[PDB]
Image (tube, rainbow, N blue to C red):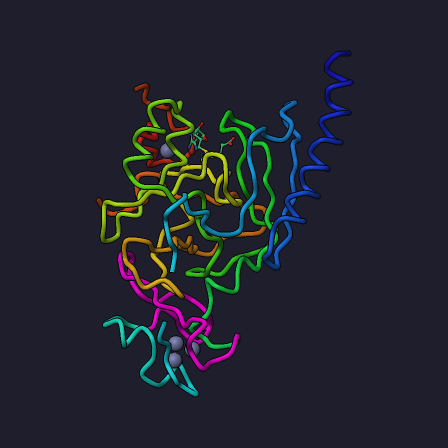
Amino acid sequence: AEYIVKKAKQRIALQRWQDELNRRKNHKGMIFVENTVDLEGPPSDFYYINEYKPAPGISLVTFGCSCTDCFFQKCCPAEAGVLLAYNKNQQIKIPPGTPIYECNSRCQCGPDCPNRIVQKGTQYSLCIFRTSNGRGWGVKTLVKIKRMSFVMEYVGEVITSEEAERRGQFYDNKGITYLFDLDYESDEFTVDAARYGNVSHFVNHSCDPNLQVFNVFIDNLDTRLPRIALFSTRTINAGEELTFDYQMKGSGRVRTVCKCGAVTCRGYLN
Ligand SMILES: C[S@@+](CC[C@H](N)C(=O)[O-])C[C@H]1O[C@@H](n2cnc3c(N)ncnc32)[C@H](O)[C@@H]1O
Ligand SMILES: [Zn+2]
Ligand SMILES: [Zn+2]
Ligand SMILES: [Zn+2]
Ligand SMILES: [Zn+2]
């Protein structure tokens, strides 16, 4: 009875939140919201952002390449001492731990350069949905995603690692999960998606995940401050939940029990 009224208002609240997410988003794919399991409405104190929101005094970002064919000429990755990340079908072909150096605002090439993938934004329609076995909100794809494909970036506030430590003291276990050290080549900065984030803010942990982190440099060449991209590790089917390994944010208190469901589940998130 109280329940029935709450369900009815919940439906309206989730619709209004979906509409707001779609106004805020700057990428091609749609964002959907669904809760067929319980009465949870939209989270409070969460603001959708498309890119890193740096703290006061933190600056994010120029030479580019001059290729007429960035796929076959000596291009931005070459200049940085690395391989081109991508094959002709937009799939990442370099191993985890290798940085992605995409072409940038200073390169001569246009949008359809095969070295401009992360920067084009998420192409897939995705749904924030309520999980059925106690893992809160999660994210699923509504369409099939090819192996080794760009899905979404991890974004949040960009703060110092010192700030994240201090913030973490007042965070519960969930809040700590929103801290993402940018430790590719430096211990200086941390992404905090707790309050400001994109759809990656709702992606759950798995012990056999279907997404994998890569560091990305576009206009930014300072390796203290990589952008973080999530690429698929395998073919992901329509309707499938997206997951990454929270322990693999980089290659560097109650223990939360892992409910990922994998046969090889490690039992705990932390
Ligand atoms: C970054 S949040 C992800 C979205 C979150 N499920 C929500 O409702 O907003 C991480 C938190 O989600 C839950 N979670 C994610 N993966 C889980 C898993 N495999 N098993 C149990 N809980 C999980 C835990 O509460 C964890 O602290
Ligand atoms: Zn080039
Ligand atoms: Zn370039
Ligand atoms: Zn290019
Ligand atoms: Zn697990």
Residue 267 as seen in the image, left or right of residue 251: right
User: Residue 40 versus residue 75: which sits nearer the camera?
Assistant: 75
Q: Quadrant of ligand 4?
A: bottom left
| Figure check: 18 above or below 71 | above
The structure residue drawn at horizontal position 31% and vertical position 65%, both measured from the top left corner, is 94
Q: Residue furthest bottom?
A: 68
User: Residue 62 versus residue 139: which sits nearer the camera?
Assistant: 62
Residue 218 x, y percent position in the rendering: 39, 65
Residue 27 x, y percent position in the rendering: 59, 57
- Tally of marks: 0
In the rendered structure, does residue 57 fall within the stretch colored magenta?
A: no
In the rendered structure, does residue 86 fall within the stretch colored magenta?
A: yes
Q: Quadrant of the N terminus?
A: top right
| Figure check: 122 above or below 76 | above
Residue 187 as seen in the image, left or right of residue 39: left
The range drawn in magenta is: 84-111
Q: Quadrant of residue 227?
A: bottom left
Residue 59 as seen in the image, left or right of residue 240: left
* Chief SS of the magenta region: loop
Residue 205 x, y percent position in the rendering: 41, 37
